[PDB]
Length: 165
Length: 133
Length: 133
Image (cartoon, rainbow over all chains, first blue to last red; front, side, top):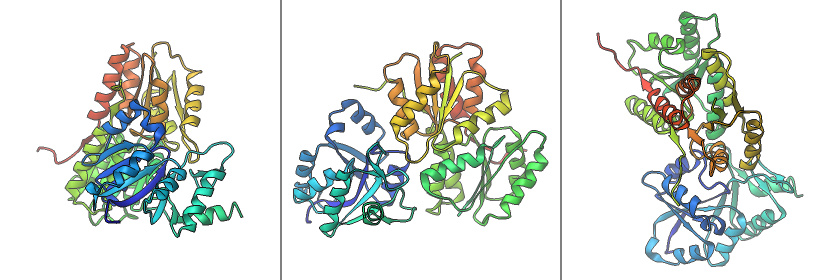
């Protein structure tokens, strides 16, 4: 808690898409953005493009889940407000297990796919994504689903409750 | 907020707004008009006026049009002529619309919004090209 | 001629083309796609490919998209990656479309067309402002 401060945790398989990162950066008052994904971290070409389109005044970083736990374990970012970008709620539960503190998780968007169920206009969940959301809720963590801060906030459990019992 | 009216030849204005709202959510204080073959600038002036009657124009009005010199542009030009806080900007594109709509909520001054719309519209035009590896 | 494919979030691409054709007459060798909530880049890649199958891509393909970084842009980026004479240009607007379609008929080289599209797109964004008297 006396270390970095998670300004917001946005889940999105697209990371930066449209003005969602620009508007969310100014509204969230975020000057730093860290991407946690082993698949992207292994793509040097994609990392270059994301780093070259990093919004002005905002820095974008690319690290893996194991490396991310260590960056947070460094008080060098204490007080610093950083935004966490994830592609799947599974990677979020992993950070929590490492002793990372998360009060709430925001679902930005998830590419739909066959075998998955559509819960929102562009949010899909599989039996694995749902299982991770249930564990976060059981820990008292709030789960909100919303594409833009200007859109009505919905509860992840409510959307999954009207689908999965 | 500052009022925004979008006008293009044809029926594209409504879709540019729809596209923006797909990105940002539904917008307030925004109007649009279409221009069909057979209509002239005078028809368009009436259309713009009917849209303005429904908008809050107290802080100003920004007409975003497709191209410099077309009828939509010419008609909008006749309306803003000796009006304070009225401007017409040609070359409307999604980057311009999105940035402009986002900034509008933070209550910028009229000159600030006009400058941002031109700058973001131009900076939004960019080719991918080969990328470094 | 060089093939042009237009892609934007929502349903604006078809209208931008319609607007252009209202100015220039019906166009050949032009395709477009829409992007609906629920779709992903992979869906869009298929849509782009289906459009390309119907186009003459021998001289090259220019994807004109709404904004840098959106799904339409991301999917187009994956297609042009190691292809010669394939490019993606964000910020599509009417001045860019009109100038590009006009020049295309005079059979310019691919690099020439790409450069013209970016330049006309940017120069097309212009505010009226006060005029000299």
